[PDB]
Length: 50
Image 1 (cartoon, rainbow, N blue to C red):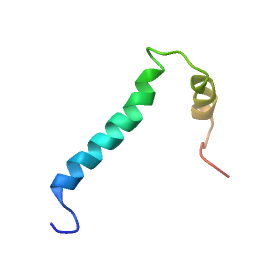
Image 2: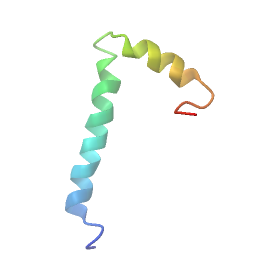
Image 3: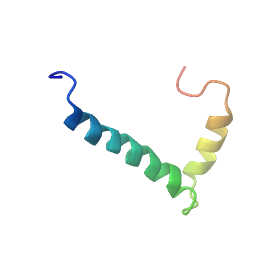
């Protein structure tokens, strides 16, 4: 498990969970403009970039 270490896996997961959850939940208890863009962007058929 050299290339794929667990110690680095866990910490890596928290970075994504909190990194994405922070802004995802921030909208719940923190109204902002980003929510507007994310709203329409999420409704889109295929978000991302052309």
